[PDB]
Length: 88
Length: 88
Image 1 (cartoon, each protein chain N blue to C red):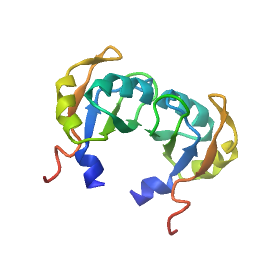
Image 2 (cartoon, rainbow over the protein chains, first blue to last red):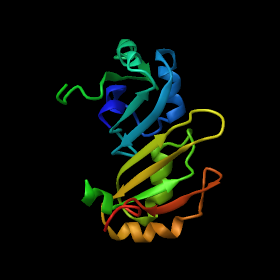
Image 3 (tube, chains in turn orange, blue):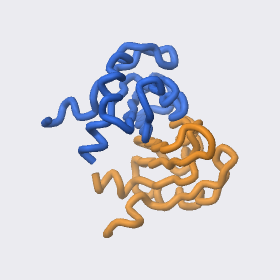
């Protein structure tokens, strides 16, 4: 829901070989993670997918923003709050 | 939405090392896959997570039911229609 979403980030430029363990490991230093959701629309060739990371605390979202443009599995990831293009 | 959900299955007993490519490969014979969603609540130790597979055609859901109790990454998976515990 909206409260879980307020504690979540969108992570762009994720590939079809990414695992939840790898993603949690990348964001571990930002704080405790409740849930990792990976959404893939391509399963071979050029990838097409993203993830949501739901943190336990809201302050971890702000912290995680420093990981925008960081290298994850050899690709620069995009990190924004999950509710960015949503009212509030 | 409800129409995407009607073309989707829930897959239980998925672990934090599962990839979308592996999951699509397991269900490939059932028909074309639109999207794989992996949802993990544990990232080490005993796993806790599941997935949704959204097929291109609704008939692929029925076909995929034969994969209930099949071995995926060394574990017996649970396959049910995504809207099972939902009205319709």
